[PDB]
Length: 388
Ligand SMILES: CC(C)CCC[C@@H](C)[C@H]1CC[C@H]2[C@@H]3CC=C4C[C@@H](O)CC[C@]4(C)[C@H]3CC[C@]12C
Ligand SMILES: CC(C)CCC[C@@H](C)[C@H]1CC[C@H]2[C@@H]3CC=C4C[C@@H](O)CC[C@]4(C)[C@H]3CC[C@]12C
Ligand SMILES: CC(C)CCC[C@@H](C)[C@H]1CC[C@H]2[C@@H]3CC=C4C[C@@H](O)CC[C@]4(C)[C@H]3CC[C@]12C
Ligand SMILES: CCCCCCCC/C=C\CCCCCCCC(=O)OC[C@H](O)CO
Ligand SMILES: Nc1nc(NCCc2ccc(O)cc2)nc2nc(-c3ccco3)nn12
Ligand SMILES: CCCCCCCC/C=C\CCCCCCCC(=O)O
Ligand code: NA
Image (cartoon, rainbow, N blue to C red; front, side, top):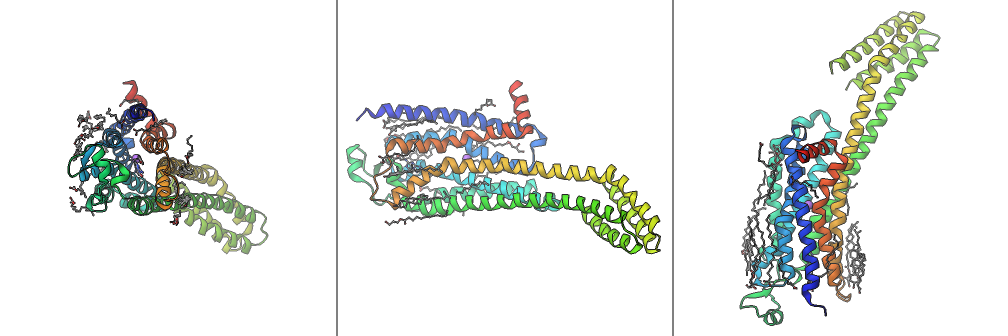
């Protein structure tokens, strides 16, 4: 039985190193958004709420974790707060992560209404509500779902605790049914699975929209060929009718409108000549469409594909963030499930408990790195900030 201060010393030093790094990186995120108007958008207001939660892991939840690892004598309700505050911060992260995912789904599914529907003012109201809800969920044990009514009095007396105090230890005061059913299943795993569903819808929508862009391009070009080797006016007509419909369809910014105006106009010219039974004149007219395609429609296609690919890249960055939160927190939640559902199983050993706790805390360090590696406007703003 090694002096407890030695293992304690390692755990505490590591927690402190994590806290420094969580503060530094996430302050840098907040400073970048504050300084750069190109980063000031609704998506990034949720990014900042998430960075604030991670700053608070460093300033408060890690000092609290260090404290409760000592098992110091405390009033049971003050102990609860120490124990549970980190659950407020985690819940808030889950809400910011779910908000980010929904925001990106709206942006790809209804880009036309996104700006009128998702506003900064509404985003700030939603962030305030989510913080209130996170306090309610994470401090639910302080509302009575706790083990304070059943204190471990032999353990309190061995440590010399005073009357009404307990040894302040996480699994002595926080019920494991709360941790597994309420906190993990309902409040963590359900949201994370919802996030997964949303990201699946974002990526399927992008892939549908890119395939439609290419279809339309291919349709335009096939129908041109159809026209070229048509032999009677009626065939030219049918293929122009399909082109016209697709054109007004693809229509759904001045240099872009002028291109589709030319396009539809030239189709109409050709249709009219076809309807008068002037096949050669119609085919020649239709050939002019090639100039418009080269000088306008291709540029349209290329910019639309590029916007979509940017949205896909951005949605992957956001999903990496959500996936890393799951990876860092799931080991602890899974251990709790073993403790709870398998009372015939030996408790996970202390070294693994503390490993799982610091892994969860490390999540508060990783997001600024994902932003720097994957989002140029962040990377570049971090550079300017650091260089200055
Ligand atoms: C705004 C920020 C900086 C304020 C942080 C205040 C924190 C540190 C305060 C607020 C509530 C406090 C707890 C309230 C009650 C008790 C019970 C007592 O037997 C041991 C201390 C303990 C467990 C306190 C520890 C310190 C505590 C957690
Ligand atoms: C990649 C992430 C999401 C998955 C991590 C899975 C981890 C947490 C799993 C894999 C194997 C598991 C261990 C398997 C066996 C035991 C022995 C039992 O008496 C206590 C629990 C304990 C010690 C488990 C704790 C949780 C555990 C370490
Ligand atoms: C990973 C994502 C998809 C979902 C989360 C999976 C969780 C809920 C699963 C994965 C492994 C599971 C554990 C595997 C083994 C046992 C031992 C058994 O005696 C009690 C249930 C218990 C402790 C399971 C509880 C639930 C569990 C922890
Ligand atoms: C805005 C930034 C401000 C920074 C804020 C600092 C963070 C708080 C640090 C530690 C709190 C945890 C320490 C609680 C320790 C309690 C120790 C104690 O109470 O010992 C009594 C003994 O057990 C007999 O009752
Ligand atoms: N199970 C658990 N324990 C602890 N700390 C106590 C570790 C321990 C466990 C058993 C023991 O006899 C002595 C120490 N912190 C904890 N934090 C969490 C947590 C936060 C979010 C999900 O789980 N679970 N959790
Ligand atoms: C930026 C400001 C952040 C301030 C962080 C302060 C650092 C405090 C570190 C941990 C405090 C742990 C106290 C240990 C509990 C007492 C042990 C006992 O009574 O037996
Ligand atoms: Na977080």
